[PDB]
Length: 295
Figure 1 (cartoon, helix red, strand yellow):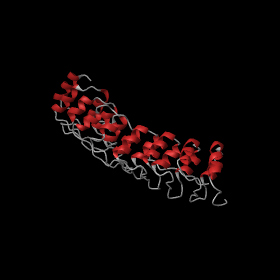
Figure 2 (spheres, rainbow, N blue to C red):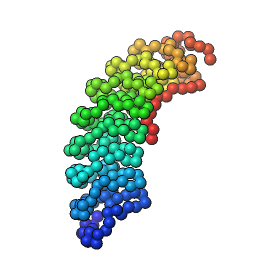
Figure 3 (cartoon, one colour):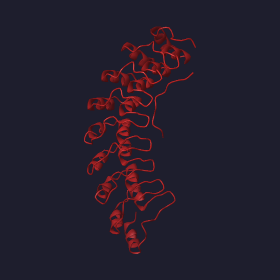
Figure 4 (cartoon, rainbow, N blue to C red):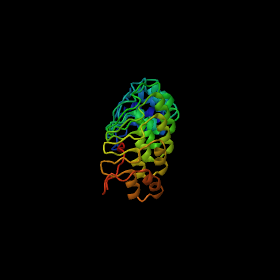
């Protein structure tokens, strides 16, 4: 970060195509190390921000990983990359949400933002924002207009992920906005099913209030009970049963919530579930897990 040295290098016309084996650009180290006085020097030679290496990364993507936003706010008029994805198809929106800077939403709001762009998985920036579910996100995301609950390849809707992490705040914000409470996955799992597998009574109570069905069955017969029993989360199973969840529902494999609780040797659960459950629909080991976005 010696700026007058770079001024000396400028008259010698060093190329701005200086590319390493890792795919870095001269803009990337200025984005990382926060040595930024040379940025106006780099634009004296009319630098172009659109530059993607082997990993397809942009100055904004490297900038948001370690944010010195004063450069980015001025790069945006200097032909900034509005919807640039990474090699993973990742937009700056959801990675900025996961990094969760306080003004990065305002930084993109200076231009705008798209929180529905498809990744290589099919996940939207709205869904990855809801997965972290920060405090300012549920306020700011309102200004952006996007599908409130957006499925992925799995069919995972923001509500589903919120139930997975059991973030009550986000689950509230989302229900208030009018997202689908019982949104289903490609296999047929709802945010209740998923919360019951998680075993979070809070992430289940909230959903009960949201009116997600307590007997929502999967395409293979698994219900939020079967799931709480396989998980061994007696708390969630009791919360379901108390709220009317049926305990005598046979799945596509012939195992009820009791059958499962038993096979898994969970006794605390088996005591309530086995008695609440009626006699097993059939005389007799495939489990049931909700979908999740891949790495």
